Image 1 (cartoon, rainbow over the protein chains, first blue to last red):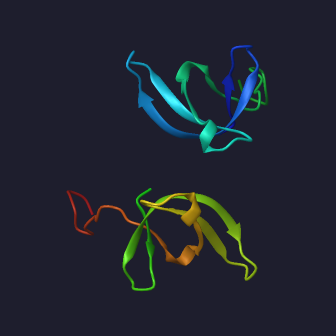
Image 2 (image 1 turned 180 degrees about the vertical axis):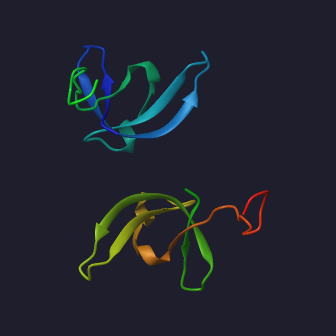
Image 3 (image 1 turned 90 degrees about the vertical axis):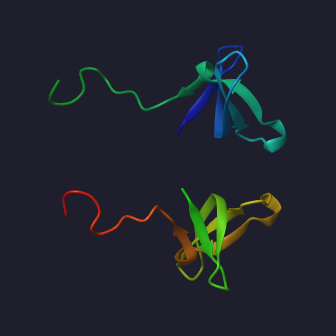
Length: 66
Length: 66
């Protein structure tokens, strides 16, 4: 899904996959993240607001029709 | 995906998930299967022709229109 996590530095960290999902005790969604280059021992629960999906850029004024 | 593997007995075995996919040396597709109730140590490469998707049955003559 070309998923990236925005870390404390603002730098993006590549996500291998989402392992699981839960609602936390504050009522907010978290995902259990498999980090690229790591195994299940390093999987961590992360807030959804920091998980990004990056797609190729598409220019507002791209192509034939607007 | 409600996936099931049809085993040597003809009995269906529940698949937790598909871990990976490859074309084998005979030219046929295989999937690396995570078996329900098992861990990655028991993952095995299985032929696609034995992997089933089971959905609720829908009767040819169900509902209002044909």
